[PDB]
Amino acid sequence: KETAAAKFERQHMDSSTSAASSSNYCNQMMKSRNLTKDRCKPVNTFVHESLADVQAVCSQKNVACKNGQTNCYQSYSTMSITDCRETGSSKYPNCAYKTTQANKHIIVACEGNPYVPVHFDASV
């Protein structure tokens, strides 16, 4: 079964670009990472930094997770991210998203050895 670390990379890492270039990045990315498989995942964030830089967040600003656990961490730096949010009219299986590029701090839950992100909690 996919490791939570690998699932995080599939769902949230896109170290290719520095940003979202096109307005259907999300339509394309949400497909190619298997997030429009069975249903349209409504909301999802892609991080446009190195994996190393994202993993390093696990040694940055410790914060509570939304679920009240205390193994979350806020990136000290803003990061290039793309917020994908399904449109109001989107209907599976033709999943449609707005793409919003932004530079924000990320909050991730970290776990395991190596101690890496297993969950994307928020961006701030």
Image (cartoon, rainbow, N blue to C red):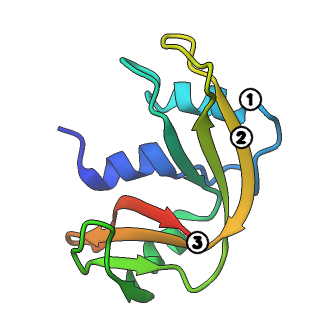
Residue 22: percent from left, percent from top: 82, 36
Residue that badge 1 annotates: 24
Q: Quadrant of the N terminus?
A: top left
Q: Residue at x 48, y 32 (%)?
A: 33
Q: Nearer the viewer, residue 62 or 18?
A: 62
Q: Quadrant of the C terminus?
A: bottom right
Callout 1 amino acid: Asn
Would you say the residues marked 2 and 1 are in contact, meaning their CB atoms lie under 8 Å apart? yes
Callout 3 amino acid: Val
Would you say the residues marked 3 and 1 are in contact, meaning their CB atoms lie under 8 Å apart? no
Are there few (<14), some (14-19), or many (20+) residues within 10 Å of tag 1?
some
Is residue 53 shown above or below 97? below
Residue that badge 3 annotates: 124
Are there few (<14), some (14-19), or many (20+) residues within 10 Å of tag 2?
many
Task: Determine the CA span between mark 2 and mark 1.
Answer: 7 Å
The first of marks 3 and 1 along the sequence is 1
Task: Determine the CA span between mark 3 and mark 1.
Answer: 23 Å
Residue that badge 2 annotates: 99
Callout 2 amino acid: Thr
Q: Residue at x 23, y 73 (%)?
A: 68
As drawn, the residue found furthest toward the front would be 88
Q: Secondary structure at mark 2?
A: strand
Q: Secondary structure at mark 1?
A: loop
As drawn, the residue found furthest toward the left would be 1
